[PDB]
Amino acid sequence: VTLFVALYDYEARTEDDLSFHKGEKFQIVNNTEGDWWLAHSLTTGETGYIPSNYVAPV
């Protein structure tokens, strides 16, 4: 798999997005539905949407 790392902090503003800190890592669950990706945080274990331009491949 290809993990992703947060480049910037992000504060959630909806029910289905994740808040995350710079440096947090994610496993991507789905990225075939646009620039907001369904992701699973390796820190919190939560799953939710993240803005794809806020992460980079590890």
Image (tube, rainbow, N blue to C red):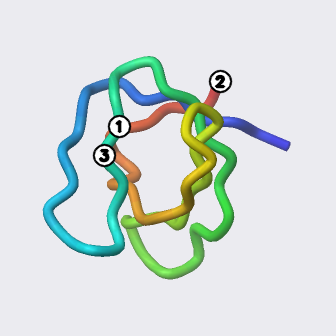
Give the image quarter of residue 28: bottom right
Q: For mark 3, does the 10 Å Cα neighbourhood hold few (<14), some (14 to 19), or many (20 or more) residues?
A: some
In the picture as drawn, the residue positioned furthest to the bottom comes out as: 33
Q: Can you identify the residue that label 2 sits on?
A: 58
The secondary element bearing badge 2 is classed as: loop
Q: Quadrant of the C terminus?
A: top right
Are dots 1 and 3 in contact, CB under 8 Å? yes
The secondary element bearing badge 3 is classed as: loop
- The answer to whether residue 57 is above or below residue 39 is above
Q: Return the x and y of residue 40 as percentages of the image width and height.
A: 61, 53
Give the foreground label among 3 and 2. 3
Q: In the image shown, does 6 or 19 lie closer to the viewer?
A: 19
Q: Amino acid at mark 1?
A: Phe
Q: Is 10 left, or right, of 30 in this rendering?
A: left
Q: Residue at x 55, y 61 (%)?
A: 47
Give the image quarter of residue 31: bottom right
Q: For mark 2, does the 10 Å Cα neighbourhood hold few (<14), some (14 to 19), or many (20 or more) residues?
A: few
Give the foreground label among 2 and 1. 1
Q: Residue at x 42, y 29 (%)?
A: 6
Q: Is 23 left, or right, of 27 in this rendering?
A: left
Q: Amino acid at mark 2?
A: Val
Q: Amino acid at mark 3?
A: Ser
Q: In the image shown, does 57 or 10 lie closer to the viewer?
A: 10
Mark closest to the chain's N terminus, 3 or 2? 3
- The answer to whether residue 15 is above or below residue 27 is below
> Separation of disc 2 and disc 1 at Cα?
16 Å
Q: Can you identify the residue that label 1 sits on?
A: 20
Residue 2: which numbered mark, if any?
none
Q: Return the x and y of residue 12 as percentages of the image width and height.
A: 21, 55
Q: Can you identify the residue that label 3 sits on?
A: 19
